[PDB]
Length: 51
Length: 51
Image 1 (cartoon, rainbow over the protein chains, first blue to last red):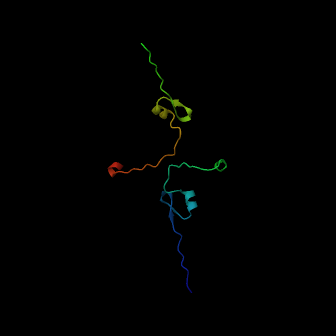
Image 2: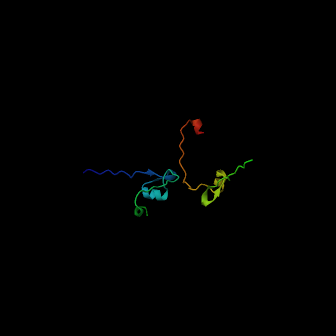
Image 3: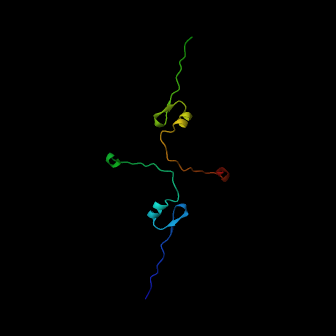
């Protein structure tokens, strides 16, 4: 009669040195660890794809 | 005896469509045409270069 072994969910870090588990929830609450200044995007394709 | 003509200093465009003759003054009054989001600076050098 073997017994299964459970391991607790790992803790990942987030902004301001705080730890959460869900990435979406931690991002929506705290956000990324490193904050970029902002990036400009580029698109190649048809006018319909652009709009 | 012959005359010599003068050309006025041209005006370079700036923010909001305004223009000025001096680039530094036009920047200080209006600013650049395209406002970037900022850039991450990269430095290669000594720690004395760092400070």
